Image (spheres, grey):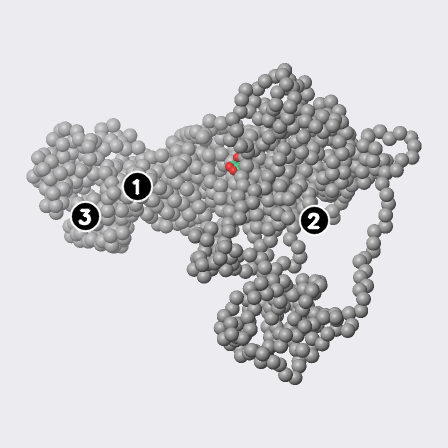
Amino acid sequence: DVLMTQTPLSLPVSLGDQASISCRSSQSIVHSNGNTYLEWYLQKPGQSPKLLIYKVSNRFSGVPDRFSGSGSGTDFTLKISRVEAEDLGVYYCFQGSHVPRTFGGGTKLEIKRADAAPTVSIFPPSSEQLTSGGASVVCFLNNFYPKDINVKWKIDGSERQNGVLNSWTDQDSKDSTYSMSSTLTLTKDEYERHNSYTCEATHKTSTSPIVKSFNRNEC
Amino acid sequence: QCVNLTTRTQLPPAYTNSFTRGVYYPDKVFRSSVLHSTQDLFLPFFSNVTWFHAIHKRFDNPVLPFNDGVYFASTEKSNIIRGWIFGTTLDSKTQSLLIVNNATNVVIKVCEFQFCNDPFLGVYYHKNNKSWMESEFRVYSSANNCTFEYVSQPFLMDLEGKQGNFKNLREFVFKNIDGYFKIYSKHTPINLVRDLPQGFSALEPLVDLPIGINITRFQTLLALHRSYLTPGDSSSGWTAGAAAYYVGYLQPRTFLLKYNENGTITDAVDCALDPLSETKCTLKSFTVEKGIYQTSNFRVQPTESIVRFPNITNLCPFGEVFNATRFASVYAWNRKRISNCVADYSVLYNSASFSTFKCYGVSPTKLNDLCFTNVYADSFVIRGDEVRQIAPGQTGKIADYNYKLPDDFTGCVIAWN
Amino acid sequence: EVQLLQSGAELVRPGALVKLSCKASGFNIKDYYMHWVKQRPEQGLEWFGWIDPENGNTIYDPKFQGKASITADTSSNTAYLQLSSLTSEDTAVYYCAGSGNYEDAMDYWGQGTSVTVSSAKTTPPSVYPLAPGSAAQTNSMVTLGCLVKGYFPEPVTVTWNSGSLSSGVHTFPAVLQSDLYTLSSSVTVPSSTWPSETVTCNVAHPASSTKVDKKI
Amino acid sequence: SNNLDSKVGGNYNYLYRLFRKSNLKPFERDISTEIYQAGSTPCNGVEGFNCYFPLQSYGFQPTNGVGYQPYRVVVLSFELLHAPATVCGPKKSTNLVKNKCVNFNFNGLTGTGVLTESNKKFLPFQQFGRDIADTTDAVRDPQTL
Ligand SMILES: *[C@@H]1O[C@H](CO)[C@@H](O)[C@H](O)[C@H]1NC(C)=O
């Protein structure tokens, strides 16, 4: 049993920049002959992990020449000469040879772009959903960068954390932006018991979160 | 399993000489300060033993006849020798005895093992702890019908490579006595460049294997090497270390076992090797004084067995009886007494001129080599359905009412179309 | 070209067993090792074990030791995986690798299989339209959304106008909560499109063969 | 065993070798099914004239006579003092006595002599010792080595 740690969790790099991903191991993996035992895996969106480098010093066949690794001891680093748009994914480190194989924590990569504030849009539950007995307040946060973002719900001025789910989209192929939505699960009685509903979008680019609200009686 | 090695190359069975190897304790009886004479399957001194070695483009794993027994001797540094495979066909067709040292303990099993082209054991990807513990089991694919199993004490086997001369010497004896297998072991350090050291050693029992199977061939297992850096095709791209092992043959010879004060054997004499050794065996002493002594008696063995029996002429007309113009009725069967002549049964039994032939009590072949006291012939003709009634302890219209054969009838029945 | 094929997804109740197959194509199963992996959204990748079809020896992660067994079929050139005494924690995506040739320099991965361990059964999705809220909120462009909740199992695809409208369309991956999946979609259009022009969201659930069209 | 082995007109589970190409050796079990050739004509592995199938079935029957009824036969073979004792009869053992003339029965070896601590060192596998005359010299106690 060997424990492996990775840092940083994620890092941005503009097209043509150099990306550095480091891995740490709790035990030495180098041996007498001098070679290193490790593999690098990259899992692109909608695709399974694929090998990039083996032995840290030799590139896997068919891989672009930009991918290359270096290091010694238990601390290594993966260097990419020129990062392209096809490098999106999660980087992993692998321990081979004859031993319970270990995996890394993962390292995500993204393309740098100008900061953009989120577009906050909030919609009330449909009449059909209320007839069915359920309710769900939906808030849309789109066209924001970086991915770091948060949403706060408030019912009649009171915060409610239960029933909140968020999902982050993959990097856009055209705008290179990120989109997220916040869904607040509420029963029919709970939804009809309150009128004012607010969705606050907290983003780094703006000190004051963008706030959108609606009234149940007005919808 | 069946993948052949890439670098393996066949070599002729070169031979080498041994000084005094082949000496072992016949049994558990203890003796000291005495010279004991015993006869058993032994490897003759100054005999020829196969010269085999294992390297990265010649890998030796041949099949050698077992006969009544064989002798083993090998010089090792990293203990490349893994074990052996014993059996008649070395396949699931019959039971095969196997001994494997897989870095934890000596394992002996007797089952129906599936034959492999190059059976062996090895290890892979050691990195920063040598380990060298069994990784793959290519010895056989499957086993069934296991009648015996044994386990020895645990131990760690050092397969790490070493430089310099050969620091280890292992010699085993394998033999079969009425199905009872006996294994003898010896382990001593040596400093050898090539071939074998010049000296004497005594082998001691290792395990008792009252299995009881016929073994006519055996194989020698070897341990290969693997690494993260230089692998190969599965499993043809694997290589083994440098080692040399030799295989001998045991013959029923008589040795003079010289026992010291502690009972260990310090010297041995092979009677059939040297006429001086013959004199020692006759005198039952390890020292021969100057003079002339009588050891045995020479004799010339016969070239071949020559048999000159008298003429077998004057044969009684058995052919006339079988081919007579007429035969008596079944109820009136004639009783013919035959004597004062010779009988040639080769032309009768082996001519295949009759539809059916059978004998009761004595096989037809044995009757040709026997001398009788009285011989009688009963000739009769019966229907086809009634032929089955001609036998001891039968009943029916013929067996009971016409002609009955006693239950102790030692004669034969002859019939044809 | 080497390719590894596995089942798209599997569903089993707690305490049952699931058998997975990893087909081998373009390479010899006997002469190359096989590996297995478990992936979770929070824990990333988790190693499971390895097997050699020629030998058959298997080593398992101390986490899963005694929890599963690995087998391979030489004639069919397919590697089989079996999991027993399944529970909720076993929900994850499984992958297989091989073609090592006793060397780390070559390995490949398949598309993987999504295995969910829960007592829930197939549930058709409930699609509802999401219209704009209070009129106090106005902008030069209007935003629309489609709500999908209470469906199982994944995947479920949501699009707009049968995929004919790709402008300002964002697809949000589903989120698992209380053994249920929930996803939403949003489309941004100018004020000259809605409500002047109809906007529809299409939701497809291949597992339940459910297709719903809702106009906003 | 007529009450058990006999079954109706015969029992095929019990068979015997009627013919063999030569004389059998002691403690030799031959299960070969090769056809016994009596004449000069090859049998071609099939039955025929001067060709008989060595394996045959008994005529065991419940009504057979004393001589024809089946009798189960068991033969016990053993080696005495030729190896370490693995079996022994239900004979109670007593305490050991030293420096006295006593009648000793060790591992099936019976004799009279004086038992004393021995200065000779036996090997781990060696159990029975012998003198120059080959008579009994020393032995190892089976219970406490
Ligand atoms: C060695 O052989 C024994 C025989 O049963 C087996 O149980 C064991 O797993 C093998 N390997 C080791 C390391 O003992």
Q: In this rendering, do the residues under marks 3 and 2 share a single chain?
A: no
Q: Which chain is disc 2 placed on?
A: B
Q: Residues within 10 Å of mark 1 (few under 14, many from 20)?
A: some
Question: Which mark is drawn over residue C169?
Answer: none
Q: Nearer the viewer, residue A190 or B133?
A: B133
**Quarter of the image that includes the N terminus of chain A:** top left
Would residue B90 appear left or right of A199 to someone viewing this image? right
The numbered mark at residue C126 is 3
Residue C201 percent across, percent down from the top left? 21, 51
The amino acid pointed to by label 3 is Ser
Q: Is mark 1 within 8 Å of ligand 1?
A: no
Residue B5 seen: no
The amino acid at mark 1 is Gly
Instruction: Give the letter of the chain under mark 1.
Output: C
Image location (x, y in percent) of residue B396 = 49, 73
Say which residue label 2 marks: B10
CA–CA distance in space, label 2 to label 1: 56 Å
Disc nearer the start of the sequence (1/3): 1
From the viewer's perspective, is the residue at label 3 or at label 2 nearer?
A: 2
Image height of C112 relative to A109, above or below: below
The image position of residue D106, as x and y in percent, is 60, 26
Residue placed most toward the observer, A143 or D73: D73
Label 1: which residue?
A: C15
Question: Who is closer to the viewer here, B313 or C5?
Answer: B313
Above or below, D131 relative to A108: above
Q: Position of residue A88 (x, y in %)?
A: 39, 41
